[PDB]
Length: 162
Image (cartoon, rainbow, N blue to C red; front, side, top):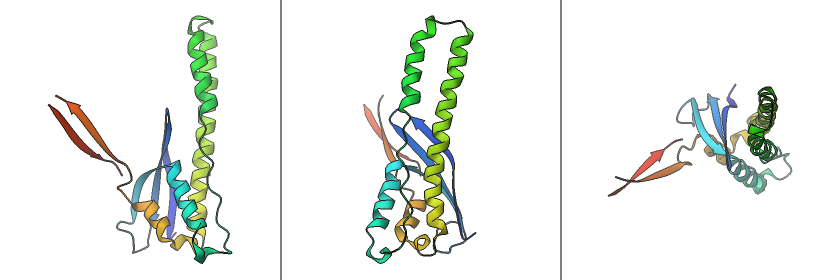
């Protein structure tokens, strides 16, 4: 109960998957006992690389890194189906669309679980759960600074999304 992590939601975009990493904790070192941050697969790879290279963890079993999210099969089949929009019986597209969405969903389930299990294994570990880089991964809120540039005369707006 000292450190509970889950991934309540994820966003699949064209070239990206974003995970919401949600932490409940009683550790006094954190700013808040419960918080959420947005992380991408590469942030998980950075964390795993960092653990792997820490001299003090030599001989400890470090949980495997999560597998890269691959939505290519579903998206390619989505693109192909849009072509037969004029080539089927008003049901067949519908049935084709449902199968495509099941395939998306099956990918989502697998990739969220892989990324989630990785964090949960770290949280279970008597030594690794104390790792400072692991703590930064969970609570640092400046990882996704985005700027909007708009022409009304041009104005640039900072957009802050933890």
